[PDB]
Length: 150
Length: 150
Length: 150
Length: 150
Image (cartoon, rainbow over all chains, first blue to last red; front, side, top):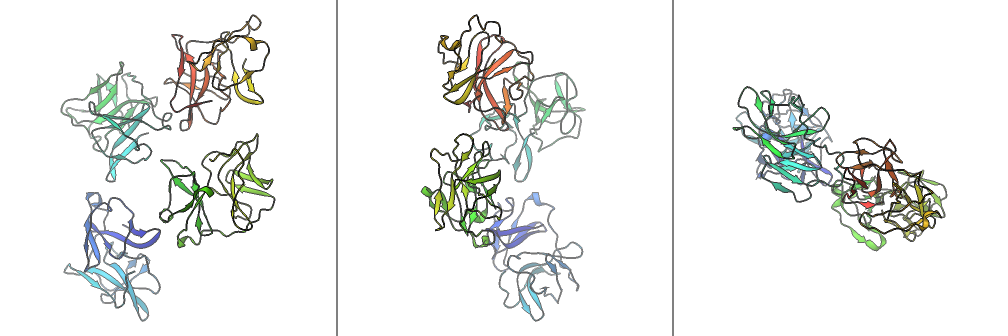
């Protein structure tokens, strides 16, 4: 469920395999900790800042299915918790920095929603940059102002 | 024991360092997940489905030996109990498959009598494709007709 | 603190770090273990029997800091201890084989002043070649004549 | 009655007798510590790395004698035992070293089964080269490749 993207001994990003294949940020480069999914050739999409490429039948069921069901409430995160603020996901103060790219969130039912790019603070608690899907089934970015790539 | 062969992550068969040097069946292909033994040219013998190679200077002692000793009785194997009656090898139904290409059967003493290739079933009990020594040092082939090797 | 060398399914020599720098012996060949540690290049000085280089600055919390004295006493070591006589360093009978050239020695307070390269046996006690330091700070070899590198 | 051979203060190998004939290696130079049989004329043979001798009518009774047949099993050695199967005399390393070329291996009955010459290292054991003779009685020498003799 987790596959890092590191380079020469420092953390740079963490990939995921969602619903049938994988994705990975584009400002994160170097070593990935497999040779199966490293052997594939990857198609890059510059507008959503995530590349996509298919994984073989060897990964037929170890993936994590996704949804768009986000009612207001608290969900779990890899280094803490989130807060649904009208489609603007957010991160507690100081938590999360360099080497936290592609980290997924997870709901109360075992469903993945959000992929991350960076973050920026406004007032009392830091907002973060989201890649998510809607009820119609098309993908969204919700990027804050001044959110540099982590 | 034996050493496995890894095509694209998962199991294919087992390479037997047996009787003093290296043998691997020609039915399955792939490379070995052990680095000191695949650093040399390995010649082939495509007559009767086995490959012949060397071993380095540290596998003469622990390598299990062969003596073509045939009392007709119940031998043992990792997935059942193979035996030699009427000039045949047999296991009951619902056994083996792909990935089991080259696992040897042994005896009560703890040495090898035979190395399995595979086969199929035609009759009430499944026969097995095998490469087995005889009294005159002949590697005679016992395989029933209509059985593709595993 | 001691990082080995990958040869063919065994170890040939070893390598350590000091003061923000790197060791290697000339007679020790082969690929080093760590991703950040191989990619830095070696400004080598082979006739002084050390291949130095600069280490990553993420390794600033692993190196050591020294002085250059050697008071009489006893020096512990991986294979027991090494004793201090004649202003020299000699290993007892039988102890010490091949491949340990590259690994350091220690004292009670735990600071390396000396690293091992060779060996020379006259009767019982064996005198091995040691790189140590001047109070001016220049490399020093106490090589016996008729020595032998491990 | 194993006899010592020493050159000018050092120990290089030991001397043996069987059947009334003094066989010693031509591996290392070395002189005899006795006045009796130091003048026995010999005929230098370099086929087997061994060379015979002669016993007068003073030591004609106390000569340990030989055997031509051998059963598979364990034996009596100066530092342990040895097993014999697959045409092999091998012992693990640690026991036995330099100065052992010319120490007799013998059966528990008390007959000289063979006389060693040296051998090689192999993993956890040592393939030990030897000279012996089968049921034909022709003197056989065993040459493991990769062996520097003792």
